Image: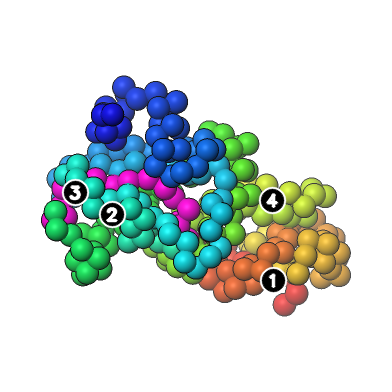
Amino acid sequence: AQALWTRNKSEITDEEYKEFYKHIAHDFNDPLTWSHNRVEGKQEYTSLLYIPSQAPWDMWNRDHKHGLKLYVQRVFIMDDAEQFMPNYLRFVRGLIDSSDLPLNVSREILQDSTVTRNLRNALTKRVLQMLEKLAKDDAEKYQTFWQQFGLVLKEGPAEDFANQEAIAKLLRFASTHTDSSAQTVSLEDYVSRMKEGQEKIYYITADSYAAAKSSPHLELLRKKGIEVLLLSDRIDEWMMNYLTEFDGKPFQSVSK
């Protein structure tokens, strides 16, 4: 029962990582991906972070116990430590074994420490890096991710200005480009087929895909041969108050 996270990366099999996820998360589904990292110097810790393949049962309950398992110098402090992730990444499971925090660390010390805020931001970037790698390396698994967690990730644009570019690149949308309600379109995809002279990313929000797809505000862009993102989730109108540019291109509602 050697602590998995203390072993060398190159010496841990993929099946050991998936079994360890199931072990620490009480989940019988394999994780989609993970990141195992040892950090030294300014901050010193090991992190092992997982993306589940399925949303947890209590995810939409405010009082969902979530977060990471915290260890200090191999000594267990607490589970479900929410201080290490932003709320839009509350699905991430895993552990942090820190050498910077004191053995008597408390929730009081956690919120007062500049250590925690820096650690949370570093771990955030590690998660975004992991998801970007998944999106590139395994599209089928990324689509599963998006189906399970996209609505949570859409909280990110308002919560986290620092990573807005990275976060935006993880979003997926339906669009007019092909006649399908599948949320397969990335903003990078959209930008890569922008027409000569097109300077904005066009969208419409509606209460459903059907309502979006059949809007008369689409007729004009369909004549210019311009793609329109079809946003039909409850969170979308609100998210678009924060996601106002991408790759230097402003967003524009087709209705205004």
Of mark 3 and mark 1, the one earlier in the sequence is 3
Q: Is residue 69 magenta?
A: no
- Name the residue type under label 4: Gln
Q: Please tell me whether mark 3 or mark 1 is closer to you in this view.
A: 3
Residue 171 occupies quadrant: bottom right
- Residue receiving disc 1: 253
The residue located at (53%, 71%) in the rendering is 242
Number of the label disc, if any, that sits on residue 78: 2
Question: In this image, 215 relative to 182: left or right?
Answer: right
Stretch in magenta = 88-102
Depicted 165 relative to depicted 236: above or below: above
Of mark 4 and mark 3, the one earlier in the sequence is 3
Q: Please tell me whether mark 2 or mark 4 is closer to you in this view.
A: 2
The CA span between labels 4 and 3 is 41 Å
Neighbours of disc 2 within 10 Å: few (<14), some (14-19), many (20+): some
Mark 2 falls on what kind of element? strand
Question: In this image, 209 relative to 149: left or right?
Answer: right
- Residue receiving disc 3: 72
The CA span between labels 2 and 4 is 38 Å
